Length: 276
Ligand SMILES: C[C@H](OP(=O)(O)OC[C@@H](O)[C@@H](O)[C@@H](O)Cn1c2nc(=O)[nH]c(=O)c-2cc2ccc(O)cc21)C(=O)N[C@@H](CCC(=O)N[C@@H](CCC(=O)O)C(=O)O)C(=O)O
Image (cartoon, rainbow, N blue to C red; front, top):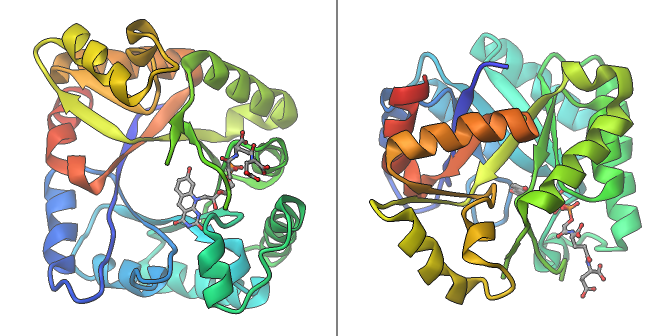
């Protein structure tokens, strides 16, 4: 599948730069602006509308909604509105919800891993029954979550890191091979209809990728330098090397929809120049 590139921006209360940041994202060649769903961050659909008003080409996506925060019927209303009032520029990523303290602040039951996945399941089923027109993305590496992506999603988002639900450990390329294979088995005949996404956490420009990886072992002692150079959540090297790495990872994992974090927007833009 042809590459699509996204940048995960954080619309921040009290910071007046949102419109400017969105314009920079488009001008730098990104295809998607992604926004998160967290307390203390601007509300995602409202921020996406503000982004749509200053950009003409990018898609806008949630990355990802906390399913506990949304009534499915009211979310379907929001998704139909965002679709119609942007001319079809909105996609919605959904997840189970990550931060317990946020559930508690909003007066919501954290429950169990099982109840949080069931909530996602119930929302996806409802959104499909209501025939929402926004493309749907499902993010997470859990068996049940990837099963839900295989059943319901237009895009599956694989996480390149694990964390205790309640900082982040990066997962090896070999564990990623297994997660993509798991997804593919669950998707069956629908596998080829689902776009595969991943979020790159760090984009490290360097003329010595090998020396960089060796130094980064201190942040990741459970891995060798060779493993670090294959981690899907890291891009290390020159832009040409990063482009070749992304080509190799599209072949290995199927990752064609690659997002980076806001802090790396300019660092990664040369790679868009080479790949497009
Ligand atoms: C928690 C996570 O599970 P997951 O299926 O990958 O993800 C579930 C949700 O977090 C996921 O659906 C999303 O809500 C998370 N999410 C966001 N969630 C949000 O709520 N808002 C966001 O803006 C958001 C952004 C986002 C972006 C990218 C991304 O990859 C995920 C994002 C995980 O790390 N699982 C690990 C660890 C599971 C584990 O072993 N847990 C232990 C350790 C915890 C303990 O000590 O008890 C246990 O439960 O006992 C694994 O599958 O191996």
